Amino acid sequence: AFSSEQFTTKLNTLEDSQESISSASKWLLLQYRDAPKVAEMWKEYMLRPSVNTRRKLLGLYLMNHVVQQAKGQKIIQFQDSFGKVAAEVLGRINQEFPRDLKKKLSRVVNILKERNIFSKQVVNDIERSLAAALEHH
Image (tube, helix red, strand yellow):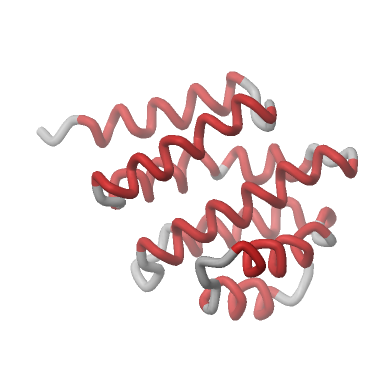
């Protein structure tokens, strides 16, 4: 519904900075209407080869800060949108991510339990996603 070029151009130029996350987060906060749109693009974007680990790590923090804020604006479409693709993206990047980043992300996944963003239905999906990568054979 919105200019996907912006979200993409920004995500591709996303850097690891406290101000950067907020800079983009603020823009996404005004995309409450593009709940499914942003989730679809973000997901398909995070599940792409071009996107590296760094880009992914940052994206997670961006969507995380945005969604968490949604609760303050009485928004649920964001949780269901980013949540339905969270178990997939997170589980896809968690397996591709190194043992080092695994901890950085693992600690982030728990944060969701504190803010109570997604429900047990979604959380149960994320865990299962990792369980699959846990086995090599």
